[PDB]
Length: 345
Image (cartoon, rainbow, N blue to C red; front, side, top):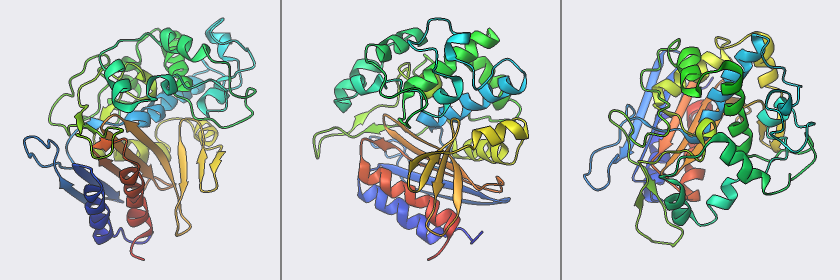
């Protein structure tokens, strides 16, 4: 790979601040040489600087943790990717042709309940932030709508899929997802900044606060740090750090977290758009210089995350801005992947 471009990374972060992120940061693990940059504030009311060791909410990056646990169950013979979801969760879904592989690749047709929830950004956050939902509650919300396509037939990203994933982990293992994450991922990789504390609202230790951008242009930011994330759970509630997400995607892509057979199933790409794919709880992004990287993005109120690694895991990048509902910042933060993998133009 080209060398990571720290001046390019610096410009990306500075642009994200100019577009309304209070803070923005990035950590590259380049085959044992670290790059770390941050600009702006973790807490905009006190002025405390953001830094690459601050913990934060990773949002939908959680789906990759869920998928690693499910693929280890596949390795253990407890789960078959091509079995019906209802084989393990009887009568859960209206159609038995919905399979575990279609759920994990967003090909199931299940309606995303969060489209009910967040049609208005701050009112929807204020609705869910202090609620505790069961898995079944969220599935029932989805099922008020019919499916959006035939099973397997179309890519349609849906949080519901990874709510099903959490129910499957808990049903098959008899343990909570927190326990399975801890035992199969956080402890073995020594992810000391990584937690799943649902439904607690506190982020343990020093963290970035999250600032939700309101729908009204120019409106005051809303502190969204503390919430249950119960509307997402196994689809979105993990807390981590840039070092720990680098560690995690490096371990995944270098083959440390499941058999080679299952990693190969995880990387069977469904087309998302002309420069992206979706595997099993895993994203592929195609970068301008002709390299692809592998990992996941997250959007949770107040926090945008990108966490991607090269195919062999030897270079990993995690970028965080502590705002959300700000598509200028979301698009700018994607540019950290170009600077960190493609290097100087």
